[PDB]
Image 1 (tube, protein in one colour):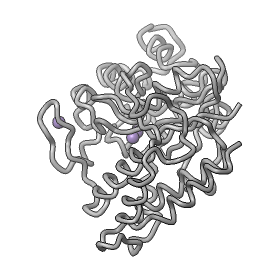
Image 2 (cartoon, rainbow, N blue to C red):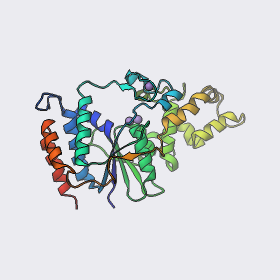
Image 3 (tube, rainbow, N blue to C red):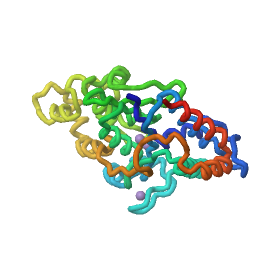
Amino acid sequence: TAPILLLDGASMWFRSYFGVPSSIKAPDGRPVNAVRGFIDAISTLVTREKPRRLVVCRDDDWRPQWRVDLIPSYKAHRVAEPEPDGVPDIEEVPDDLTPQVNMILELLDAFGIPTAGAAGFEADDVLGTLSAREERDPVVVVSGDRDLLQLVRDEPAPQVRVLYLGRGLAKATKWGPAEVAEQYGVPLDRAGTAYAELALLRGDPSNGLPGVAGIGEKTAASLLAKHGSLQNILDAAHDPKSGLSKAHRTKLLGAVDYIAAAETVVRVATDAPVTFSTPTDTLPLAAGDPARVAELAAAYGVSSSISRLQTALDQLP
Ligand SMILES: [Mn+2]
Ligand SMILES: [Mn+2]
Ligand SMILES: [Mn+2]
């Protein structure tokens, strides 16, 4: 059967912002390069993957307070203005990109393309929750964010793949457990979860996470190779006769608190309370509100992109 596409919205429209020139502008002069690129990526995906189901996943909270409480440096270098509890922090985002996010969300809503979010969670968590719950169709998670490699799955069916956007969409290929195992040296039988344990240990500068000092990617992969899992590695450290080196024991034991905190920060949630903007995740084959879509697309200078999307939809069997 055809896959369900789960789109990491912010990953994709940030990529469109930096991959489409800012001289692409609306009639009022505001850049719409991210709008154009994001709509064009949806049309490309519809044509390449021919889904019947498609969801754009939102960041209802891009920097959840529960993660910051565990690790205060989490995404700290990306905050423009921190906001008190209950209110998402203001992310440092180019001034001419935020209005384009509003334009995109307005078009998706008027078209009826499903969007999903969960209060207090990231799009990463929405993607992890929807891919964990999927029982009917193969899942394609579309993102430039290597965090989501932890979601790859062969069994139980259906499979989960990440269409990874690190080199852009034209060059993107589907990552499964084999690809993550081959490119990162984690065990194949639990490749996705072990990738998250690898990232926890080595650190993640784009998320503001330091990792465990002294355990680089090479060491963490080999430790996972020999012991199979992070839990087994901590067991080897806590047990004073295991074959774990004393230097490794010192680095791991000196980080027990960070490791316990980081575990829930690094893993994406799989049971977030996701809500949809639409009744189902079915991809509409025509605009839910065509007059509003035409008025918005003209106002946002992307009428030809919307027309291209409708042609791709028209070609779906
Ligand atoms: Mn805050
Ligand atoms: Mn994200
Ligand atoms: Mn992420």
